[PDB]
Length: 108
Length: 110
Ligand SMILES: CCCCCCCCCCCCCCCC(=O)O
Ligand SMILES: CCCCCCCCCCCCCCCC(=O)O
Ligand SMILES: CCCCCCCCCCCCCCCC(=O)O
Image (cartoon, rainbow over all chains, first blue to last red; front, side, top):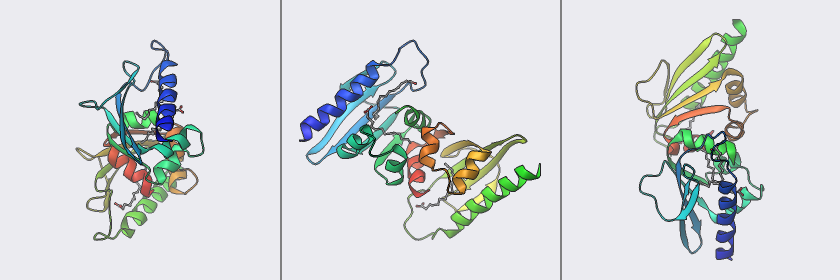
């Protein structure tokens, strides 16, 4: 169901963010607003890659905003859908800083 | 060098063919000016792809919506259908700045 699916994707993002070495080489320093479209409503999360924290909310001036459907997120996570294909199919909506967006695409 | 010249001309002819194909009054979602910087061994080839007016010109635009910096061989492969824009990004082959919405809308239309 929706809640288990959302919880799963968020825990996976939290694991990846926690795996970053704060002092190691880093390219993606920004705050990402994540809007997850679900059949029930939108789940709103803040992925702060500068401070390395993931919190629920809507950040005031995110560097990048990402809006994507839940099922597509799960597909990208399990590698049944590539980011380039998701892009080609118009499955991701972005606003904000193109540089930070491109650098994110490189590390997913 | 002739090899570089032919590759650049081919890239630009292809972009011009594509932009000339667009119906000015049909559905359009990529309305912006893209600065295209193509790195070669002979220096940077600088081109303005204006998708608002649907013109391609050599030059450096003062304030483009998106700047795209890409190597010659990668840009050749992208224009020749052998490298997808998507895989280019994943591989870190494109440098972007500016408007993410317009960058993504462009990745959708090719
Ligand atoms: C909110 C945008 C969509 C979801 C963001 C994906 C987050 C998954 C984990 C990202 C790991 C970032 C790697 C950082 C290393 C670096 O800065 O170079
Ligand atoms: C212009 C480039 C767009 C880049 C944005 C890519 C989409 C970000 C959201 C994809 C979800 C990835 C989360 C999966 C986390 C994981 O399983 O490791
Ligand atoms: C960013 C990678 C390379 C960029 C080079 C631009 C490629 C030529 C652009 C042609 C796209 C024309 C389609 C636009 C129609 C529309 O606005 O919906």
